[PDB]
Amino acid sequence: GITPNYVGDLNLDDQFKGNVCHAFTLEAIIDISNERTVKGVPAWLPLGIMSNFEYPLAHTVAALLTGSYTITQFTHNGQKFVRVNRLGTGIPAHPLRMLREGNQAFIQNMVIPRNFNQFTYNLTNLVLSVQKLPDDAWRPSKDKLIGNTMHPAVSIHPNLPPIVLPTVKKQAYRQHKNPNNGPLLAISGILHQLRVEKVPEKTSLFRISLPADMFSVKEGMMENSPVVYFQAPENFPLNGFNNRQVVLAYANPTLSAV
Amino acid sequence: QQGITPNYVGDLNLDDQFKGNVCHAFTLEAIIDISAYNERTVKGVPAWLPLGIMSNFEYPLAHTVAALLTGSYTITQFTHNGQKFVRVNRLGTGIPAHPLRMLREGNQAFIQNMVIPRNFSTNQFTYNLTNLVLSVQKLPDDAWRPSKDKLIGNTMHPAVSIHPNLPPIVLPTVKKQAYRNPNNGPLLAISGILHQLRVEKVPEKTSLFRISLPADMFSVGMMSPVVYFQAPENFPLNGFNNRQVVLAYANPTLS
């Protein structure tokens, strides 16, 4: 296995400010290999976004940087995946899948370039990026995060988890008598107008500013515009966020991956 | 430059962070590129940099480890009273009261001749950190360690300076049965067997040495008394003979 080293703007003196969020990402160098092996392919592996109240930060960070990691491959429902493994015992209930379950899978085509089905991989180098999300990040309320309720969310790409959204203002679906539909219909109505922009001077991080006339920030954390941040690989193309759909997803991070 | 952060290697178990009686030896292991400012050439050189030994009760372990592994480090040189030092710096703000100097003060100095080989000691040479690893090793069950109040206190105690450029090793209390004017017994008793003490390198551990102490002289303290101490992994075994008895603070904030 291989352990990472660190890069980021994280401040441990704020470990007790529960409303500080970090995006966590592994950045990897991978050597690929019967014929000549290719050395130095970089890849970007989001592990999650967490706020300090969800789990002690120092443990989280210590646990991540003390881990030895491995990369493996597997097929699932006829779809090629890549699993990065953190060796040894996980930690229960942990918001981030890597520490919780002791591994994290990615669709291969989100890590290995598409000129690669007869190739094996391994980690040459590993860096753990920890970046504080800006203060304008909207984030689900504590009870939604610990609950098992599902909420309106936007699937921005089929291979990224859906982005749970703030609550939709009653005013935005006046007409609709059905309240388990209303929010959903209102969202699909502007789904295709939403603009994804890359967050600058941050790696692997994107955001969507949402219309205020539709979305309320009353239910979140951290008098300002509703905006959601999400993680995608640093090299992910901007034109690749067009296959959108509206769904109901869990906010509770312990109930979303495969 | 801007700095570099370390990688981890060790046997530390975070699940024991709340067992206050677990001790870790903390050591930076470095690769250092040395270069004559006139020459293009570079050679690289490993070095072992002890930062301290801490028990879990002295400070939350996870903060300690997270703080160490998140730090960006640099190496610099300075002279003080004519003799040459090397300072490894951890960039940014400190952690006040922290047992380990590196986190507490944001830097740690070493005599140059305990980092850089003779031949690279001169002034035409500049040093850069190329690679950094943080070793964290749990000391074995038998480690003797000063009591909590001596560690928080203001008092000095009998200690052995095993080499002039390593910090001294505070010792357990000397049994009244072992000595006699009356506030020397401890110090005199120690010097009396100082040169019979045998330093052994700890096996399956880096940068770590121990001394078994006679029980008839020393009284006991975690899971015969034994003290562990840190020296560079490549420190020579014939180099623990220049010994002296001194008084040192047990409180690691005072050093």
Image (spheres, coloured by chain):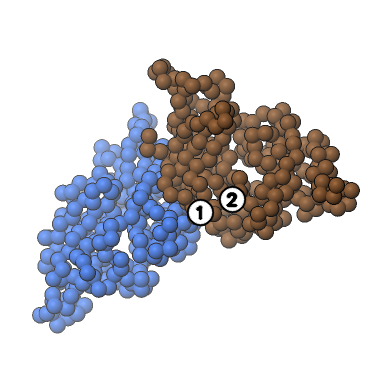
Chain colours: A blue, B brown
Left or right of B104? Residue A171 is left
The residue at the point 11 percent across, 60 percent down is A193
Relative to residue A216, is residue B35 depicted above or below? above
Q: Position of residue A97 (x, y in %)?
A: 40, 58
Q: Position of residue A185 (x, y in %)?
A: 15, 72
Q: Closer to the camera, A153 or A225?
A: A225
What amino acid type is highlighted by mark number 1?
Answer: Pro
Relative to residue A196, is residue A29 depicted above or below? above
The residue at the point 82 percent across, 36 percent down is B196
Callout 1 secondary element? loop
Q: Which residue is mark 1?
A: B96
Q: Which residue is mark 2?
A: B253
The residue at the point 30 percent across, 42 percent down is A112
Instruction: Find residue B247 and report its image quarter.
Output: top right
Callout 2 secondary element? loop
Left or right of B162? Residue B133 is left
Q: Closer to the camera, A192 or A131?
A: A131
Instruction: Find residue A27 and report its image quarter.
Output: top left
Q: Position of residue B112 (x, y in %)?
A: 56, 29
